[PDB]
Length: 215
Image (cartoon, rainbow, N blue to C red; front, side, top):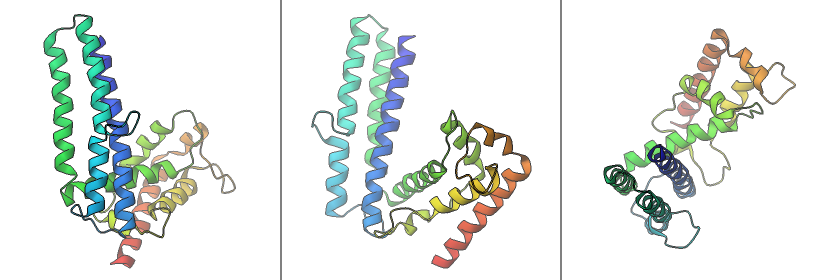
């Protein structure tokens, strides 16, 4: 029962860390107007601090590892089966291997950044209901971003242009009125087969158009 909770905490610590990591990396790609270059001085410095900063209460994988060490110590203090505890230390080591690989591979970086471009766009839809995470899971399957979504990141732009495409279409199809600029739990009743396909069609088309104009 404890093992389950510690595993959740590890998963959670890593989802937060992974997120902030990708966010930073995107300021580098953005500042380079959408060119991926994992060999630059700035990338290597940024990657190193995000993976290995020792500084207390900083956002680093190193900092996650210390947290998890305390937890595996507490598990040992309370006599939890040693197999369960090593298993956890392994997951952590595997996650560090994955990231060390991904961070220096231009295709892996593209995957991470296009996933965050989509997470950002869904978070841009102003949902004031109970559970925004659930809302976005309902929408996510109707949105598939091109492989080259990252190349539209520009230094000058505060936001990826996909934000405005998901913002507009979500309200066009799911808000009770045009005047309102927010969804809430009442909006869920507008997630009909017809509106979900039309949203899917619309977002796909606006994205195709922007991609074509760019290339």
